[PDB]
Amino acid sequence: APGSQGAPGLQGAPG
Amino acid sequence: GAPGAPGSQGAPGLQGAPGAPGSQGAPGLQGAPGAPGSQGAPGLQGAPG
């Protein structure tokens, strides 16, 4: 599963 | 007098001293797993907004 870890919010920095 | 009529031929002609080859298991060509640098969703850490 390449490129497949974002469990909590990954890539979700909205600041 | 019998001359022994010698028709004797020895029986050591067991040609095969050893047997013959047997198979064996080909070893394992490992795929070389060395890279752990998998994904982490390059999205600026875990900022809570």
Image (cartoon, coloured by chain):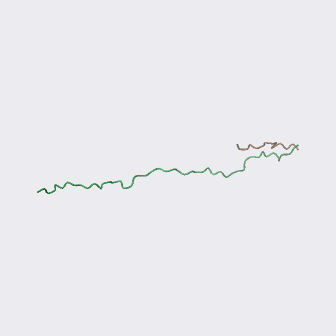
Which residue is at the far left? B1
User: Is B27 placed above or below A1 here?
Assistant: below
Q: Quadrant of the C terminus of chain A?
A: top right
In the displayed structure image, the side of residue B37 where residue B6 appears, left or right: left
Q: Quadrant of the N terminus of chain A?
A: top right
Residue B7 position, x and y percent, is: 20, 54
What is the count of numbered marks?
0
**Residue depicted at x 16% and y 56%:** B4
Which chain is assigned brown?
A: A
Q: Nearer the viewer, residue B19 or A11?
A: B19
Which residue is at the far front? B1
The answer to which quarter of the image holds residue B1 is bottom left
**Residue depicted at x 74% and y 46%:** B39
Residue B34 position, x and y percent, is: 67, 52
Which chain is assigned green?
A: B
In the displayed structure image, the side of residue B16 where residue B3 appears, left or right: left
In the displayed structure image, the side of residue B4 where residue B43 appears, left or right: right
**Residue depicted at x 60% and y 51%:** B30
**Residue depicted at x 22% and y 55%:** B8
Q: Nearer the viewer, residue B26 or B31?
A: B26
The answer to which quarter of the image holds residue B12 is bottom left
In the displayed structure image, the side of residue B20 where residue A2 appears, left or right: right
Residue B25 position, x and y percent, is: 51, 50
Residue B33 position, x and y percent, is: 65, 51
Q: Nearer the viewer, residue B15 or A14?
A: B15
